[PDB]
Length: 277
Length: 277
Ligand SMILES: CCCCCCO[C@@H]1O[C@H](CO)[C@H](O)[C@H](O)[C@H]1O[C@@H]1O[C@@H](C)[C@@H](O)[C@@H](O)[C@@H]1O
Ligand SMILES: CCCCCCO[C@@H]1O[C@H](CO)[C@H](O)[C@H](O)[C@H]1O[C@@H]1O[C@@H](C)[C@@H](O)[C@@H](O)[C@@H]1O
Ligand SMILES: O=c1ccn([C@@H]2O[C@H](COP(=O)(O)OP(=O)(O)O)[C@@H](O)[C@H]2O)c(=O)[nH]1
Ligand SMILES: O=c1ccn([C@@H]2O[C@H](COP(=O)(O)OP(=O)(O)O)[C@@H](O)[C@H]2O)c(=O)[nH]1
Ligand SMILES: [Mn+2]
Ligand SMILES: [Mn+2]
Image (cartoon, rainbow over all chains, first blue to last red; front, side):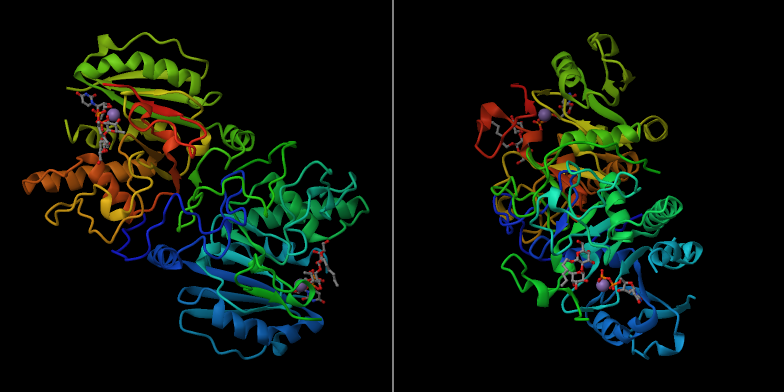
């Protein structure tokens, strides 16, 4: 049950005025594509706070990648779901190397010790019971990253993927999908909506568990058949999201590499960005 | 659980090409606004058929308005959810005046006898148990109407309203919301997203029952306080949708009066239109 929004004073949306004329802001299956200028964050914050929404964030920091945690977590505290309940789940082989990061109120961090290709999907799909009990949404991201600007409840939806920053302007035949028919991740040259990057996806706990289970099972089939998809779990993620359309798509604001790609006009904000490695 | 879509061959959506540059296609709370050119109906048909979706359509034909049923139902058969399961619920004081209309396969009609202002919301919110058992979505429309073009699963969502054709270009201070603070339907001049018309709303059975219950209760409060809202159940519908944002909004393609308003450039299709009275 959703209680009523309070009175709010904000600019009227005008039907004959779009703000964004330069980009596609809805998919052909009527999923919003999230760009700056498409959402009033005050309305969304109200909606999600009224539901006492809890967001889980999973991040893997294995071997040398524990070095990325301090900046990742400190910038998450500045930019990720501020004002909402957040539970970070840090998966690592070195619990003692997790930096001591000071968290805002309503935010928690759990260190989960693990003993590459298949680990993340397998692990997320097994934390199944814990996540269902503790959070409403799960967000699954790479650690070799920093938050530079707002990443908030505008992303939340049953299932989302993020447009890969190298391919948002590309034709589908150029997408680096797995192209060998012997792989479960196979996508022919005449199929595909978008190329989603494996570094940022999420959704409701149920839908994320469905996605990660499916990708894990498909990767195991490939392993049994002696084939490894060209971009590993990302290839499988792409196959899944082709066959199970996401209910929102994040624009490349949400996954950017400024060193590699600069700051194009179409990006009004660079929110979550690659750290050089 | 949602099974996988089959392979489909269709045009690639391109992020740097929107089709509709002339209109707002997403609300500030990230609800799609449904216009022609925003959806691939083949993808949506697949998604909803895979769930064996059943759509209920409620329509009231009381006193002289039974005369509108033949054209309403015959054109619904040509245009409304064709290929999907449909259950029409015709509420009337004259069951014998309901015309014999031939239905396509998978489609059913029930005549519900009833013995104005408050009837529709009260009645819909009591058919509660029946609707929950028989249909997945409910669509609630005026009878003094005809279908001229496709109205399909692109509308389906937990909660939708439709932009009133006289007000989609108006500023909110011009909206004919109830403006007296003594009414439960009251909306001040600095609030409001859109003016929704009472002739076409819907959603999941649960959300429609919530809306109609709330509007019925608010109308009863007004009655007890000796006030009737300026546009009756439409005023209440507008108050509800201000405080409970719809998850899709239908463009005026879905509720048009060609005699009154012609055929503006912004409307590529006239789907569901007023019959002169
Ligand atoms: C000099 C490296 C050139 C990389 C350009 C293309 O990107 C790669 O695209 C692949 C798919 O075809 C995979 O998604 C890689 O993860 C991605 O490289 C990753 O994401 C990119 C955004 C960069 O941050 C890159 O350093 C990183 O390894
Ligand atoms: C000559 C009549 C002028 C009516 C113009 C404005 O519309 C009315 O708007 C009101 C709200 O302010 C209510 O929604 C009425 O139902 C609507 O009139 C209804 O819907 C309209 C689209 C027309 O079909 C009208 O005949 C019908 O009574
Ligand atoms: O030695 C490693 C390699 C990978 N990863 C995790 O797997 C993610 C994906 O790897 P990487 O960032 O190297 O991939 P790329 O950005 O090149 O796709 C990383 O962000 C880490 O979360 C890790 O923890 N340790
Ligand atoms: O005598 C009446 C008056 C109204 N209605 C029902 O209530 C709806 C709303 O009334 P109307 O269409 O007259 O309103 P308007 O289009 O002027 O808003 C009609 O379409 C009918 O479904 C009816 O059945 N009999
Ligand atoms: Mn990375
Ligand atoms: Mn009418």
